[PDB]
C-alpha cells in the first residue's frame, strides 16, 4: 500500500496537469476575446501559472510548457508532438481550450530528474 | 582541452538542432502550398526527421519535438514557452519557417538524462 502511494506521489498524473492547465487558461484568458497585442500577455500568464503550479506540486520533474493562441478566422490549426524519453516515468498532457473566437493549445511535459 | 571537447559533445548545441529542424522542415514541406489534408503528414514527417537526427547525434538527451503548421490568412501567430530545468545542461531551440501561404513553428527540447 505504501509503495503504491509513493509511486502515485512520484508519477506524472495527466488529470491534475490538465486541471492545472485549464485553470491557468481560464484565469489568464477566461471570457476575453482574441486581441493580437494581448496574445503576448495571455500566453505569458498561462505558461507562468502552469509552471508555478507544476513546481508547487513538488514532484521531481523538469517541466516544459508550450502555449499556442490562434485566431478563429477559418485558419487550420494542427499541433503534433512526438518525443523520445522513458515512458515509465515521463509524461505529457495536451489541453485544447476554445471560445467563440480563439484556440488555446497548451502542452505540458514532465521529465523525471 | 579534453574537458572542453567532452562538454561540447554532451552539450545541447542550439545551432545544430536548428539546422536539423530546418532540414526536416525543408524535406517534409519544401515549396508546397498549404493543404489542410497534408498538414498531418508534414507535421509527422518534420517531427520524425528531427527526432531521428537528434537521436543520431548520440547525445544523452531526451528529445521533445513539437510542430505547428498553419495557413497564412492574416491571423497573427504567437507561440510561447517557459520551463523549469537545470539551465546548465538542458536546452531548447525554436525554429520559425514560412512561405507565401503558411507559418511553421517547431520547438525542440533536449533534457539531460
Image (spheres, coloured by chain):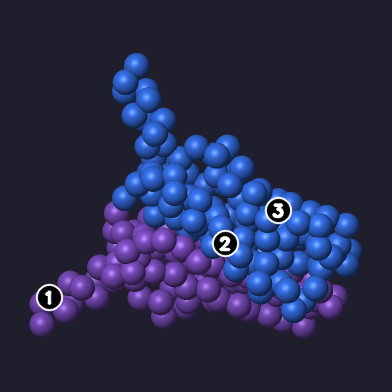
Chain colours: A purple, B blue
Residue nearest the viewer, comparing A4 with A34: A4
| 3D distance between C-alphas at marks 3 and 1 | 49 Å
Q: From the viewer's perspective, is residue B37 above or below residue B92?
A: below
Q: What element carries label 2?
A: helix
Compared to residue A103, the image places residue A53 above or below, namely: above
CA gap between label 3 and label 2 equals 12 Å
Q: Mark 1 lies on which chain?
A: A
Which label's residue is closer to the chain start, 3 or 2? 3
Residue corresponding to mark 1: A3
Same chain? Circles 1 and 2 = no
Residue B42 percent across, percent down from the top left:
67, 67
Q: Residue at x 37, y 37 (%)?
A: B10
Which residue shows up at 32% across the image and 20% down it?
B2
Q: How far apart are marks 1 and 2 (CA)?
A: 37 Å
What residue is disc 2 on? B47
Chain bearing mark 3: B
Q: Give the residue at mark 3.
A: B26
Amino acid at each position: 500500500m505504501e509503495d503504491y502511494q509513493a509511486a502515485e506521489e512520484t508519477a506524472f498524473v495527466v488529470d491534475e496537469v490538465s486541471n492545472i492547465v485549464k485553470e491557468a487558461i481560464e484565469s489568464a484568458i477566461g471570457g476575453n476575446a482574441y486581441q493580437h497585442s494581448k496574445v503576448n500577455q495571455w500566453t505569458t500568464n498561462v505558461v507562468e501559472q502552469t509552471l508555478s503550479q507544476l513546481t508547487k506540486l513538488g514532484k521531481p520533474f523538469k517541466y516544459i510548457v508550450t502555449c499556442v493562441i490562434m485566431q478563429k478566422n477559418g485558419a487550420g490549426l494542427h499541433t503534433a508532438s512526438s518525443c523520445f524519453w522513458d515512458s515509465s516515468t515521463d509524461g505529457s498532457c495536451t489541453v485544447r481550450w476554445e471560445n467563440k473566437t480563439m484556440y488555446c493549445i497548451v502542452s505540458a511535459f514532465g521529465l523525471s530528474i
